[PDB]
Amino acid sequence: LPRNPSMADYEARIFTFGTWIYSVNKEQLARAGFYALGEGDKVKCFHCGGGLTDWKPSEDPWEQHAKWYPGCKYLLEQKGQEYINNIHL
Amino acid sequence: AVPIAQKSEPHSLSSEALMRRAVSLVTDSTSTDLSQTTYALIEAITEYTKAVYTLTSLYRQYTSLLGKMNSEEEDEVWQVIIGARAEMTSKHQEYLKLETTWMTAVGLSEMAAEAAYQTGADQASITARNHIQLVKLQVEEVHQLSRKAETKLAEAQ
């Protein structure tokens, strides 16, 4: 079960990046389950509650969710286990 | 046939006693936390919603004044939208925090209800089960009203 069911929707999550000043793409972040925390480039997954900061210019949000929070069930539901596993190699 | 009238074993496993009291203390503790957290969450969603439709009205007005305003005015209207945006964000943040907490309280209440059920305490089971039921109903409804407001803000953007 997600830690924040209210952010289970993509539109709900993307609405939080209305004023985003970073190069990391907000649609991709929202697609990877993240919503902005409203401070810096800090984002958090609506499901696993995992938070990420200090993004890099060209970074893959899904790659980072699998990297840091491999246990997120939203992540495997969307990317599958082989994807997460490949990231851990 | 008729049932066999009996009774002799005390049914005294220490585990049995511990389990029954545990079920009772926990069903009460979760009852308390569920009511308390559901109230706080609904209140935060209501306050967040206010911050949303306030910004929605600010936008509807600024839109209405498009052209009618001049340099300094358009700037002053915008500073107000900036401060309003920031308020809504802070209220949203607080609401998400409490939504997670309520999720835990609900989970913990369901655990207790299931335990009371397992141990045969149907009364405590049903009460908690009916309580969780109501609290879920009300929180979904307030969230839906909250979505309505969010959609209007978006439409006004």
Image (cartoon, coloured by chain):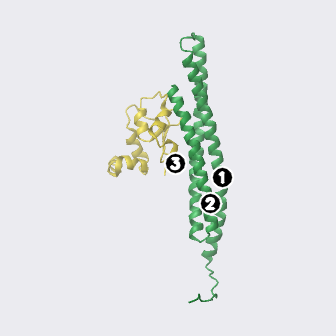
Chain colours: A yellow, B green
Name the side, left or right, on which B8 lies relative to A82: right
Going by the image, does B70 lie left or right of A51?
A: right
Asked if labels 1 and 2 share a chain, the reply is yes
**Can residue B114 be spotted in the picture?**
yes
For the residues carrying marks 3 and 2, which lies nearer the camera in this image? Answer: 2
Task: State the SS at label 2.
Answer: helix
The label shown at residue B105 is: none
Host chain of mark 1: B
Query: The residue marked by circle 2 belongs to what chain?
Result: B
Q: Which residue is mark 1?
A: B35
The picture places residue B70, in percent across and down from the top left corner, at 57, 9
Residue type at tag 3: Arg
Does dot 1 land on a helix, a strand or a loop?
helix
The reply, left or right, for residue B89 in relation to residue A50 is right
Q: CA distance from mark 3 to mark 1?
A: 19 Å
State how far apart marks 1 and 2 are (Cα). Answer: 11 Å
Q: Position of residue B42 (x, y in %)?
A: 62, 44
Mark seen at residue A3: 3
Calculate the distance from the C-alpha at mark 3 to the C-alpha at mark 2.
Answer: 22 Å
Percent x, y of residue B132: 60, 55
The residue carrying mark 2 is: B128
What's the chain of the residue with tag 3?
Answer: A
| Residue at (58% x, 37% y) in the render | B92
A22 in relation to B142, above or below: above
Same subunit, labels 3 and 1: the answer reads: no
Query: Closer to the observer: label 3 or label 1?
Result: 1
Judge by depth and name the residue closer to the eye, A57 or B27: B27
Residue A60, percent from left and from top: 37, 37
